[PDB]
Image (tube, rainbow, N blue to C red; front, side, top):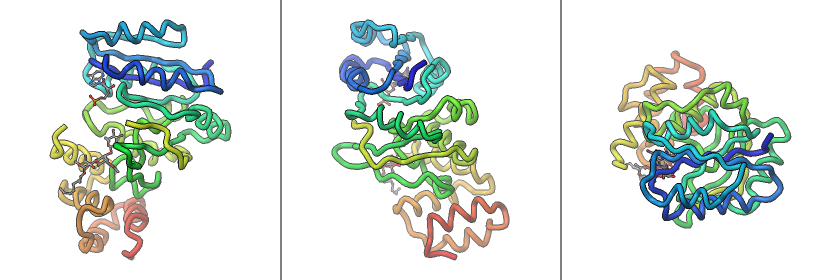
Length: 257
Ligand SMILES: CCCCCCCCO[C@@H]1O[C@@H](C)[C@@H](O)[C@@H](O[C@H]2O[C@H](C)[C@H](O)[C@H](O[C@@H]3O[C@H](CO)[C@@H](O)[C@H](O)[C@H]3O)[C@@H]2OC(C)=O)[C@@H]1O
Ligand SMILES: Nc1nc2c(ncn2[C@@H]2O[C@H](COP(=O)(O)O)[C@@H](O)[C@H]2O)c(=O)[nH]1
């Protein structure tokens, strides 16, 4: 089979899809499959992709219901041991795929790296229960997940048009999926009210006893956006509900007990 499958959802990505594909095809030391899931682009996207005429490239081009619908189609079609998702405006750095393969050959089901955004490292968090009161702990495009991880966790939830990837990683955490974080840049490259609303909803899916405002308080508090003096009240209010919730808060807020 293939060591790696890269799923690349595209729509009107003619400006950058070529650089994206070049960053994948240059990866040495792995057998790689590429699945481009195009949403019906009217521009030169499909032409550019097909200029990469190869058998390890599959092109799907049909209307879909958004980015995560396309991602789900690509993940379902992947035949690589480890599956990555790369956007058409993103690029993998040199040697990332061999690093992924190296770390996966030891049994780990998820390998994630760092993300460079506008010349800055994404402010990642640990893959652990504390992530469940926050967003996605690493950049989604820096994440590689095995076939077994996807089989166990499932596909992305189309109800979350923005933060389905966070919701997926939280399900991974709750399913005890093993993760290895690599301290190397793997990848370089919407209303804010909407992003926050989805992020709070995802957290409520972990802890459904939470009111929306309590999920927002925890998210802002872990992210360093808001105060944390109420954390002990939330813990006393809900600590009886779930040890996983207690673990998340005491990992995220070590000063509290
Ligand atoms: C109301 C005042 C409190 C402070 C507000 C936030 C400060 C500025 O933050 C920026 O705007 C908000 C809306 C977010 O867009 C921030 O992005 C981070 O927080 C998000 C919740 C999200 O976790 C995001 O990571 C990306 O998430 C998407 C969807 O899950 C994912 O596809 C990408 O791969 C992730 O990079 C950001 O998280 C971090 C640690 O950067 C934004 O910074
Ligand atoms: N297949 C598909 N891809 C999309 C859709 N919307 C955005 N994309 C692609 O998903 C990635 C995210 O880019 P964004 O538009 O979120 O900045 C890019 O590769 C973009 O071309 C869509 O509706 N369908």
